[PDB]
Image (cartoon, grey):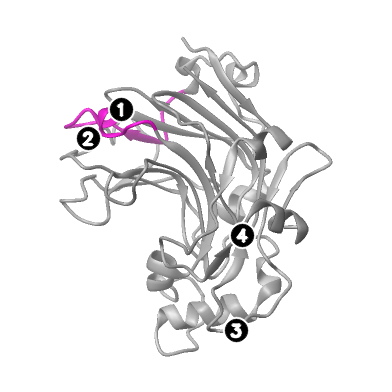
Amino acid sequence: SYTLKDSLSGKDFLDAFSFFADRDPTNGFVHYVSREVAEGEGLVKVTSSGSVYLGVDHTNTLSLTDIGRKSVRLESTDKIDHGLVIADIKHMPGSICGAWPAFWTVGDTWPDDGEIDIIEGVNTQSQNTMVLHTKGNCEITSDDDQTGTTTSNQCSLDAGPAGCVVQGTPGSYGSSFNEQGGGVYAMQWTDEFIKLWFFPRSAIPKSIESDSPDVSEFGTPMGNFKGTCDIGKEFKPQKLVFDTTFCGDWAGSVYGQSDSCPLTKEDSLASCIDFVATKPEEFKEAYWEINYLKTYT
């Protein structure tokens, strides 16, 4: 079994992350700001229930040639290397045109060392998309010990840009996740596999609640990244990252397709920027509320 490594909530949680404040690597219409700026403008706070709020500017109307809408990107100071990660999340950014939230892991370079995307989606998406990108040839083949649905089975960067993608079940992302009070996302990382689970609020395994996790009671993973390579050996120690960007590489390119998002400008990216710049009130729900983050070895 597993020993508790870090237990992070409230101010201690915030103190355990650095705030990335440079131009978005994913080219989003976002203005990532430092912690003191975020706290001053209400983007970051500890709530009265003890959770951590990470939100965006939902007040100001912006120029189309502004850097972007203000947000934050937190990267853990300490790295994780195998073991368990348990994130109890009350709220994540909603199913909102332009939005691109992510809970993910990254090494010292990006994107070419690969990454583990635990929670990720764009625009008005309603179900989570779990994604791995690996350096090595890795085909995931465990679609029959997994509740999610594999939509792309090759993880390697060399094989293509999509990576290996598993779609989560209803209620696992965005507005649907929020209205049921979120839940817990869990990752188990071993040499052979990375397994991801989502446990809806009021349906969280008791061993997680007791800080003595028994993976046997987790049941079937939602995403089972296991197959033709030792998946977990594809990654060096990783930083954990929470962010919300806007538009950019993914959200901006698919904006307006089957998502009810309005096309107002010369292409989808420009239309995305128009929405994000001119509709600040639509982003009131584009926030994370994180109860805790616990890691185990």
Q: CA distance from mark 4 to mark 3?
A: 18 Å
Q: Which mark is residue 33?
A: 4
- What residue is pinned by disc 2? 141
Q: Would you place residue 160 above or below residue 2 in this image?
A: below
Question: Could you tell me how many numbered marks the image carries?
Answer: 4
Q: Are marks 2 and 1 in contact (CB under 8 Å)?
A: no
Q: CA distance from mark 2 to mark 1?
A: 11 Å
In this view of the protein, can residue 291 be seen by the observer?
no
Spot occupied by residue 45 in the image (x, y as percentages of width and height): 75, 48
Q: Residue furthest top?
A: 1
| First in sequence: mark 4 vs mark 2 | 4
Q: Which mark is residue 63?
A: 3
Q: Is residue 65 left or right of residue 266?
A: right
Q: Would you place residue 250 above or below residue 243 in this image?
A: below
| First in sequence: mark 3 vs mark 2 | 3
Mark 1 burial class by Cα count in 10 Å: few <14, some 14-19, many 20+: many
Q: Identity of the amino acid at label 3?
A: Ser
Residue 205 falls in image quadrant: top right
SS of the residue under disc 1: loop
| First in sequence: mark 1 vs mark 3 | 3
Residue 254 falls in image quadrant: bottom left
Q: CA distance from mark 3 to mark 2?
A: 47 Å
Q: Which mark is residue 179?
A: none
Q: Of residues 216 and 88, which is closer to you in this image?
A: 88
Q: Residue at x 55, y 57 (%)?
A: 21
SS of the residue under disc 3: loop
- What residue is pinned by disc 1? 193
Q: Residue at x 54, y 82 (%)?
A: 274
Q: Identity of the amino acid at label 2?
A: Thr
Q: CA distance from mark 1 to mark 4?
A: 35 Å
Spot occupied by residue 20 in the image (x, y as percentages of width and height): 53, 52
Q: Identity of the amino acid at label 1?
A: Phe
